[PDB]
Amino acid sequence: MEKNFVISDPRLPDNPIIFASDSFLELTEYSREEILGRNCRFLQGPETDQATVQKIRDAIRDQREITVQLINYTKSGKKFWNLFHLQPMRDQKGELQYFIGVQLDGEFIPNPLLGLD
Ligand SMILES: Cc1cc2nc3c(=O)[nH]c(=O)nc-3n(C[C@H](O)[C@H](O)[C@H](O)COP(=O)(O)O)c2cc1C
Image 1 (spheres, rainbow, N blue to C red):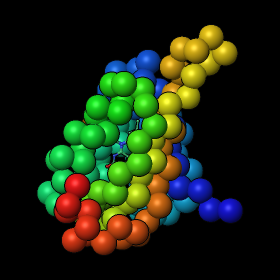
Image 2: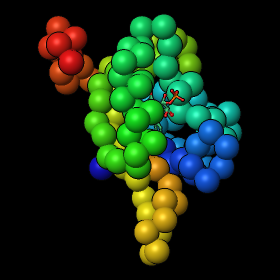
Image 3: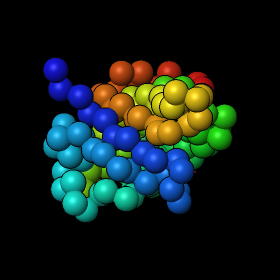
């Protein structure tokens, strides 16, 4: 099955991407070489709701799983709705090791209802 995902290392400065799936690269139109080491906020742009970005920032702080829908942009500037699922990954001793972020492309939640959040 097709899997859009990236893995970040929160033990390195500003939670850089250390792995991006082929499907993620195809969705976003970026090369692997040009996004390794980036914070995944590079997918955001003007239309991205900063209230939703705050919800992600809080979930990362608390190391809790969250799903949000927000506007992201391809390399060529095409807007897409991203239903984004964040999962903390802990080592055998319960210490945070990675985050994995899974992206589903689509306006799953209609914008008019999303706006009631
Ligand atoms: C593993 C992982 C994957 C992420 N994937 C996305 C994404 O696909 N789209 C997006 O807008 N933000 C994504 N983010 C969120 C941003 O990297 C960042 O955490 C968010 O914008 C909140 O922090 P900031 O206020 O410092 O930007 C992801 C974060 C992590 C840790």
